[PDB]
Each structure stands twice: as structure tokens, then as C-alpha cells.
């Protein structure tokens, strides 16, 4: 199925890059711990791979993709609470139903 990765920044740096490939309904998860008010910016090379974030103080999830209305002018989202957050990378249901695949590179920035 999908893979579950703990995001681990190089010390003194505020981003990390991952690559993956999702098949069908699989989703990959990128987990991290952060403080209320830190800003997250996620960019992904394949816009056919959705990027949604789950965690404390977030009802349901938030779309972090580049055109999402949840983002501010700098493409950032402010974490509403401190704790463990989960970025999920997944295909649309349409593509998942067709057992399509998405190769992707994702850059996760947390400041
Ligand atoms: Na999960
Ligand atoms: Na980024
Ligand atoms: Na769909």
C-alpha cells in the first residue's frame, strides 16, 4: 500500500524533499510535529497528486495544493495547534478508480 514517512529535516533547515509513487487508492503519509503558528508550504511536481493535511485543531482536512483557497498569499498555511500533523498524498477518486499511478516529488517546508 502507501508508505508512511516521518519527516526529518536536516538540522537547521526548514524543508525536506521526498519522492514516491502512488497506485490506485493508495496514499502516502508524511508525518511531523510542529508548533501552533508555524507555517507550512507544500509543493508537488505532479499536480495529479492531491496534498491534504490532517491534524489537531483542523476539522476534517485542509487542501495544501498550490491553488487552494486555504493558503495565504505566500502559499503558506498557519498551523492552528501544536502537535502531530499528517500530510497525505493521494490521487483523485477518478484516477484511483482507474488504478492509474502518480510518480511525484514533494517538497515540505515548515517554518
Ligand atoms: Na493514515
Ligand atoms: Na515547499
Ligand atoms: Na474524482
Image (cartoon, rainbow, N blue to C red):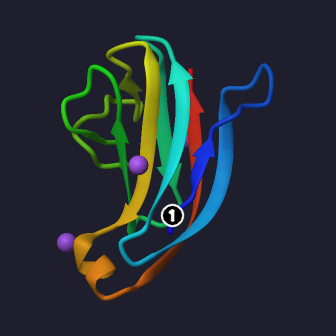
Please state the horizontal and vertical placement of residue 100, each as a whole percent of the image. Answer: 40, 85
Question: Eyeballing the image, is 28 above or below 101?
Answer: above
Helix, strand, or loop for circle 1? loop
* Residue at 63% over, 37% down: 7
* Residue at 32% over, 78% down: 96
* Residue at 49% over, 50% down: 29
- The picture quadrant where one finds residue 54 is top left
Please state the horizontal and vertical placement of residue 70, each as a whole percent of the image. Answer: 25, 35
Question: Eyeballing the image, is 65 above or below 16?
Answer: below
Q: Does the beta carbon at disc 1 come under 8 Å from ligand 1?
A: no
Please state the horizontal and vertical placement of residue 1, each as a whole percent of the image. Answer: 50, 69
- Residue at the extreme bottom: 98
Q: Quadrant of ligand 2?
A: top right
Q: Closest to the observer: 102 or 73?
A: 102
Q: Is residue 12 left or right of residue 17?
A: right
**Residue of label 1:** 2
Please state the horizontal and vertical placement of residue 72, each as a whole percent of the image. Answer: 31, 28
Quadrant holding the C terminus: top right
Question: Eyeballing the image, is 61 above or below 32?
Answer: below
Q: Is residue 48 left or right of residue 33?
A: left
Q: Is residue 106 left or right of residue 12?
A: left
Q: Is residue 64 left or right of residue 60?
A: right
Q: Closest to the observer: 20 or 1?
A: 1
* Residue at 48% over, 42% down: 42
Amino acid at each position: 500500500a502507501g508508505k508512511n514517512v516521518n519527516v526529518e529535516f536536516r538540522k537547521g533547515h526548514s524543508s525536506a524533499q521526498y519522492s514516491g509513487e502512488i497506485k490506485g487508492y493508495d496514499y502516502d503519509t508524511y508525518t511531523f510535529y510542529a508548533k501552533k503558528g508555524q507555517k507550512v508550504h507544500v509543493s508537488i511536481s505532479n499536480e495529479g497528486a492531491d496534498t491534504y493535511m490532517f491534524g489537531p485543531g483542523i476539522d476534517d482536512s485542509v487542501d495544501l495544493s498550490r491553488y487552494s483557497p486555504e493558503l495565504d498569499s505566500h502559499g503558506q498555511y498557519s498551523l492552528p495547534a501544536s502537535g502531530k500533523y499528517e500530510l497525505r498524498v493521494m490521487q483523485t477518486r477518478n484516477d484511483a478508480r482507474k488504478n492509474k499511478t502518480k510518480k511525484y516529488n514533494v517538497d515540505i517546508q515548515i517554518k
